[PDB]
Length: 196
Image (cartoon, rainbow, N blue to C red; front, side, top):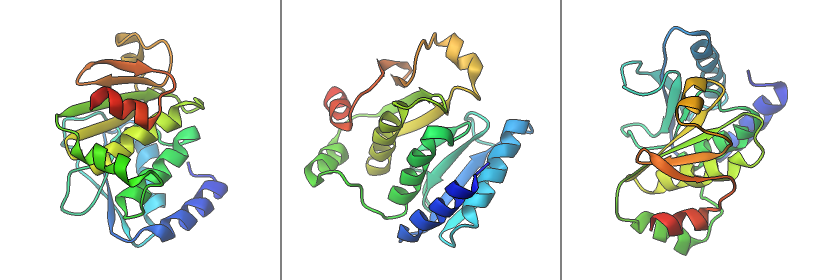
């Protein structure tokens, strides 16, 4: 759950939101799903710009949630727990989706917006992985900027079966359209060059 520090800090960052943001969860009856429901609930009462709804009908991992805008189905998705060292990645995702500008250069943002082609990214991370945030943040921003670019950040502690199934030996582990894309540290600029 959100610890006092996280909650207070989250309340502070969410003042930066300028547009309404929706957290759309897809849950099952598991205990992990209850944790996510309780977390998204706490996040939503920290700001009047954030609404927590669920649609447990979508063919996606459970539990997981979409970060988007009302009347939209575009945005990054977190499957499993978004805390640990990914708390910052969550914060940024909510900010960006809420109108707060990325700190990146404008021409890079544009190159991302102009990427042609459809890409479905999946990034496995662990809550204690210190080098996972930057990769998760890079791919989240790209999904916020280009609707043709999708990203699901997967907590390997909630989807353990996928870790051995795909033979993930370390994190972050990134896949694109079902195939291995890269592992370990990578910058946004290095990622855009590979897919551009």
